[PDB]
Image 1 (tube, chains in turn red, green):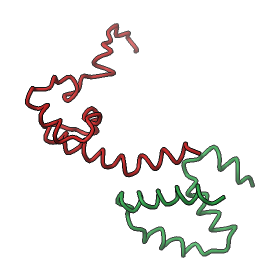
Image 2 (cartoon, one colour; image 1 turned 180 degrees about the vertical axis):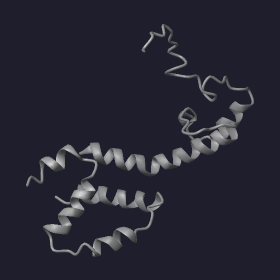
Image 3 (cartoon, chains in turn yellow, orange; image 1 turned 45 degrees about the horizontal axis):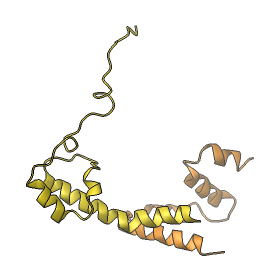
Image 4 (cartoon, helix red, strand yellow; image 1 turned 120 degrees about the vertical axis):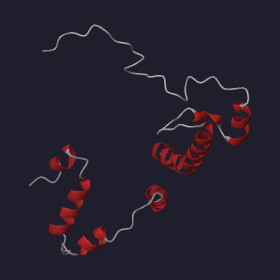
Length: 82
Length: 63
């Protein structure tokens, strides 16, 4: 039954290029990202989701930055600090 | 018979072990846990996040 396949693209079965990643930024959208995102590091993380569009990614990368500094900090720091 | 080996291999349901050991070893009724575990609010995120800081400080600051 197995019948060896002989094909594998590490780019269709592992990392699949998602919509938000692999988007060069349009010269105008940078102006929105710079004004309506507190830290741009969270524009990458996409738990969803989550198109369309950048008017949603802003709402997500702000709410995740709010969810981070409220709890992520306390939990990790405390747990590993001592 | 061994409340330890059973405790370890299954860390997922430590909740059940706690409740059962409350139920039999200690004298509490297996009715007064039922409501309080049925009456609970959903932590909804907010409640949970706060209790969780709370544990975190308290355990850490008890000596």
